[PDB]
Amino acid sequence: EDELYRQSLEIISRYLREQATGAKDTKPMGRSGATSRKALETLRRVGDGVQRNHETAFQGMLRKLDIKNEDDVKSLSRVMIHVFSDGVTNWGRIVTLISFGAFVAKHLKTINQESCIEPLAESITDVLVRTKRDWLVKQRGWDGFVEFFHVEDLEG
Ligand SMILES: CN1C/C=C/CCCCN2C[C@@]3(CCCc4cc(Cl)ccc43)COc3ccc(cc32)[C@@](O)(C(=O)O)CC1=O
C-alpha cells in the first residue's frame, strides 16, 4: 500500500474539483484524514493567492498549452515533467504545480470537459509523487506541507 500516493491523490483531486465546481466535497477523507483536511485547507488559502499573484503568467501558459480535449490533457504530463520535475524542489514550486492544475481544471469546466479533471489530478499526483518521493519523505510529506504554511494567530 502506497499511503503517500493515496493521500496525495485525495488532496490534489479534491482541490481541483472544488476549484472547478465551487462546492466543497462533504465526504470524509480516507486514511490520515486530519492531515489531509488541513492540507486541503492550506491549498485553499495558498493556491488561490498563487493564481492571482501570477495571473498574467498563468493565462499566458494556458493559452500556450491550448487545451481543447482529452488528448491535450494527456499531453500535459510531459510538460509537467519538463517544467516542474526538472528544477529545484521546494514547497512553493509544488504549490505552483497544484495551483496551475486547479487553473487548468477550471478551464476544463469552462470548455465543458469536466470529465478530464480527475485524470488530470492523477497525472499531477503521478508527477509529484513518482518524481519527488525522496524529497517529500524527507520533508515529512503532507504533515510537513501543513507545518510549512502554518500561520500563528495574531495577538490582540
Ligand atoms: C509562480 N511561478 C511562475 C508562474 C509561471 C506561470 C507558468 C506556470 C508553469 N508551471 C505549470 C506546469 C507546467 C505547464 C503545464 C502544467 C500543467 C499542470 Cl496540470 C500543472 C502544472 C503545469 C508545471 O508546474 C509548474 C511548477 C513550477 C513553476 C511553473 C510551473 C515555476 O516555479 C517555474 O517556472 O519553474 C514558476 C512559478 O512557480
Image: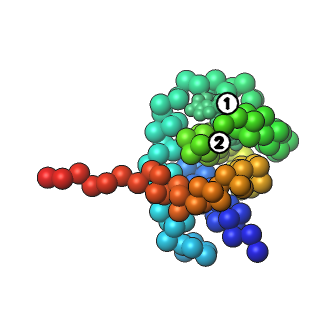
Which residue corresponds to the image point at 23% horizontal and 51% vertical from the top-left?
A: 154
Give the vertical position of 126 relative to 6 (above or below). above
Provide the secondary structure element on which disc 2 rests: loop
- In this rendering, does residue 84 appear at all? yes
Q: What is the CA distance from the residue labelled 1 to the residue labelled 2? A: 22 Å
Q: Position of residue 42 (x, y in %)?
A: 47, 54
| Residue at x-position 65% and y-position 59% | 137
Q: Which residue is mark 1?
A: 62
Q: On residue 20, which mark appears?
A: none
Q: Quadrant of residue 88?
A: top right
Percent from the top left, x then y, of residue 33?
A: 54, 72
In-image side of 112 versus 71 (left or right): left
Rendered view: 151 above or below 62 = below
Q: Residue at x 76, y 74 (%)?
A: 1
Q: Furthest residue to the front?
A: 138
Task: Please name whichever residue, 7 or 109, is drawn nearer the observer in this view of the structure.
Answer: 7
Q: Amino acid at mark 1?
A: Leu
Q: Nearer the viewer, residue 12 or 19?
A: 12
> Which mark is nearer the camera, 1 or 2?
2
In the image: residue 66, left or right of residue 57: right
Which residue carries the number 2 mark? 89
Mark 2 crowd level (few <14, some 14–19, many ≥20, 10 Å Cα): few
Mark 1 secondary-structure assignment: helix
Quadrant in which residue 8 is drawn: bottom right
Q: Residue at x 46, y 57 (%)?
A: 147
**Position of residue 136 measured from the top left corner of the image (x, y, whole percent):** 65, 55
